[PDB]
Image 1 (cartoon, each protein chain N blue to C red):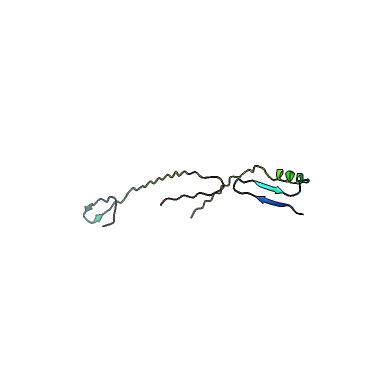
Image 2: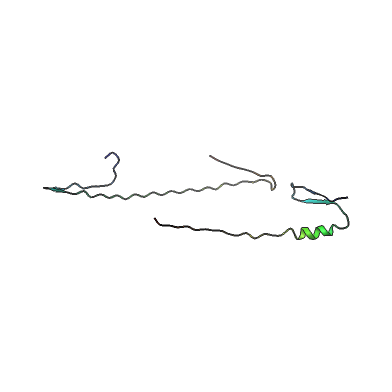
Length: 50
Length: 50
């Protein structure tokens, strides 16, 4: 019928009670959607004279 | 005079006069703040003093 995705939030895990045959189209996409992310350090400087 | 700070030296020889004026002032300030806490992952804890 449809794909019903439910997310827990209290263990930070999600379910998939949807098609029992093409779930592979979900494992691939979540695997491409869970990835460590790099972070950047920003510093700015200003100066003047009067 | 109620507010003055520093030194000044009185001199008089006949018609003239002169007043020297100087002072040095400095100020230093420090702080430090180390709070610590425990909680579970998903639920937020908050903390404050003051």
